[PDB]
Length: 11
Length: 240
Ligand SMILES: C=CC[Si](CC=C)(c1ccc(OC[C@@H](O)CCC(=O)O)c(C)c1)c1ccc(OCC(O)(CC)CC)c(C)c1
Figure 1 (spheres, each protein chain N blue to C red):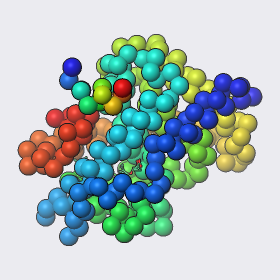
Figure 2: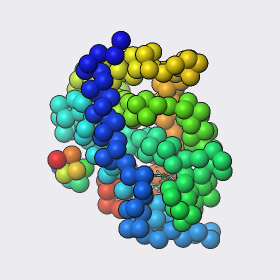
Figure 3: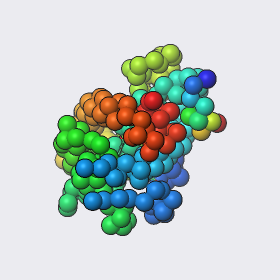
Figure 4: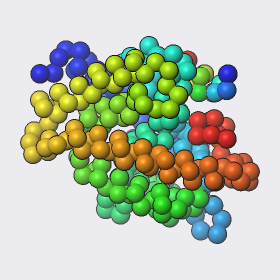
């Protein structure tokens, strides 16, 4: 959604 | 007494910290160079510093027992609201009360209140921040208590936007009971006197520090020229 780099770092 | 699951939790958190905190500070060479003298000259270097530790904080959080049992939305909510506070906590390791500075191995990477000022922040934040760093250092926490407090900070069920507050509280309770039991059995008096209550107080101090940083960050980041020196991750986590 809106936090793609946070989500990607959360695997 | 410390159950087998509780010493397992402590072992996991100790290891997670050692894997996400680098006391060599070797990656600081990759940041934009520090500029010390009017202009917010420390903002490029400190933006990269903050962005780096947000990554480290995320890595730590992913290893907290139970954290990944949450939805991705809740993990995002918890980290967006807590990253600033965990940075304040984890920075206490490099903080020294000899000169009230964050000493990260070299003079170039030795930060004091002047460097905070040269990133746009005012004594409204710096004064309670230094008092926090001093008071946290006073607790002389065991590393076990240090990592437990960072993890409790992250998994807080009252953060705004949390969906499964039931699960977030159940995760934090196992960490809270682990920390309380650890203080009883492994922290000898008088160092353990009121230690848990003093640690929880530091969580309250962090909420106020969070509030003040967020308001100064919102004012600073409103200026597009300042936003330009931030990183994409900082803008995503701390806000537009
Ligand atoms: C000059 C002041 C030093 Si700081 C004091 C602490 C609060 C500090 C000190 C040591 C640190 O090292 C942490 C380990 O994690 C690294 C080891 C590892 O992980 O390997 C970190 C991360 C921070 C600081 C300065 C600026 C700032 O923001 C400015 C901003 O608002 C400008 C808009 C946002 C960009 C923040 C939030 C904090």
